[PDB]
Length: 440
Length: 74
Image 1 (cartoon, each protein chain N blue to C red):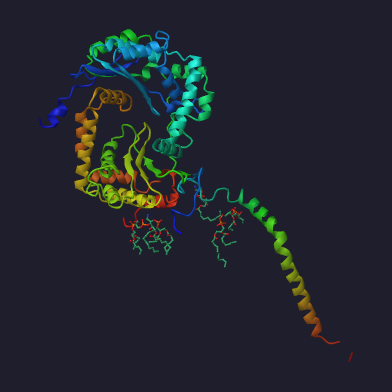
Image 2: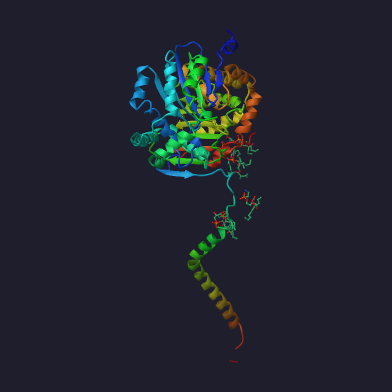
């Protein structure tokens, strides 16, 4: 077992396509469990301002009931068989995965065929879920991380569907009507933009037969998004009652395929993540982590690489007190420019190992593997094997990182989103000036 | 008196934009000129009268000095 042999000895993600365009995929390896999901290609990205938040509403209403399974009967099927049903809908993707035992894979598929195709959209249920949406949005107001990320998306992709939040404006939540939800489920849940992915012990032939016996009667064989724009700006929500000030800084990243993703993920891996409850503290190779632990100017910071199809956000988000935001911005920008101008080999090797471990450790359990399958079939158009990932990491070197960071970080107008006691946060001019180094 | 503890403010939202994306001279003449005229009209009433009083006393003083340094009573 020489690692590379293990990557070569990974079961292949077998993929087939029905006449309707359903991309069926499976990764049968050993387990008696499975995760079966249908990864839609819908989300808030494909929503007009009137329809903003319809995807969230459809996600909520999906599990309530169907015509074949009125209301709680659906739940009765999921719990009585031991299955765990779950859904998640981001800006550009939506999925309903039902974790279950591999023995009862047939029924689950049928169950899934009910949820995505034949929904209920009951009007009384619509009002009951409208109220829940409102209170849940008031809940998410408390989530500082989510609020700051939505602020970043609003200020970066302003005037574009990317700015639209997943939940939608509170006004829309009240103004959505059953006609809009029916249109959305009849316009963004079409068969071509579907990925039926199953992990665990799921034989591919059985999956194909089940899909052809349950998902056959679907749409036959246009809204295809608009290339959004990046607008260097900032949203500063100065609110001096929150104890900490969450700040998120990002630059236009790569596209979904955009092989430059592999070097950048290494570069961000060099920065790493730090918070107050970590271990080593003033010993991590990450200069930001070491400095933060030496001065306690950071409460929790991480590097994010939210990457959409035509563009993406690459940056860092940090949480700290009111008197340490400027020191943060200084050190964060300084490390960014240090990688930009002189990246050297050793930290590149560390980033390569870090990225290898991230990709390898993420792909365990039926749910993460199935999520990888469904997302890969939509974004990259193929399930990128871990061997290919290793090959793409291998040739990344110091020069490659120094050039990709130069092409993405050096002298680029950023997007900033601060919330809380963010008065100490430097104005946009100083932040923009941080992205160029007179010493260079 | 440094950034961080000047005062307390809440529920304020400030949007801005990178200087490299928005125009440096937005409507410099389309909106600049009417604004200049409005600002001029706002303060001309309270600025001019003291100076026109100066101009009046100046012209009167110079002409009276010229008149005094002359020949009449002899």
